Image 1 (cartoon, rainbow, N blue to C red):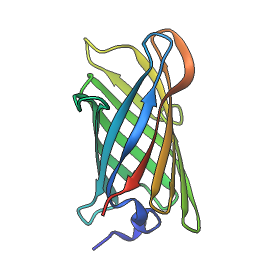
Image 2 (cartoon, helix red, strand yellow):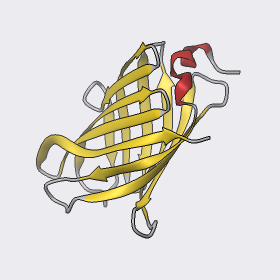
Image 3 (spheres, one colour):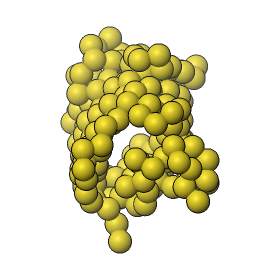
Image 4 (cartoon, rainbow, N blue to C red):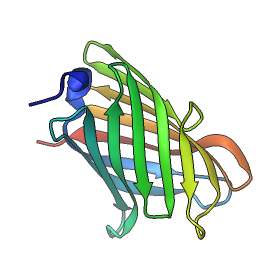
Length: 161
């Protein structure tokens, strides 16, 4: 069933929902609801899809989709497409301390960003995830549009039954 390489990350499997917030020097702050699903097809990667929407009415905001590859246990390659015309490969590592998993990834660690002709100029993304039991939280930092690498999105999600 589950590929051996994915065993440490098995607590990610399933559906998660919660709420977060975003900011950047070039935009107004905002908040969002978020739904994520992690699944697999028997190979050494997880599938991942995310949709966010406005807190007030539920209007679609951002989404992302792709794969969390486990090269060899302890190392990850996150490969993502964004509907904003951007692709992202973040590379990094994780650690398990009991029911806590900490994952740290970045495009800056031999990752990649691709920009469609009409996309905004994003040049680096860093992600820090913590899965603690039924709570998943993250912070994402971004370097883009003339601004230095800094906090951009963060959320807390909870495992759905």
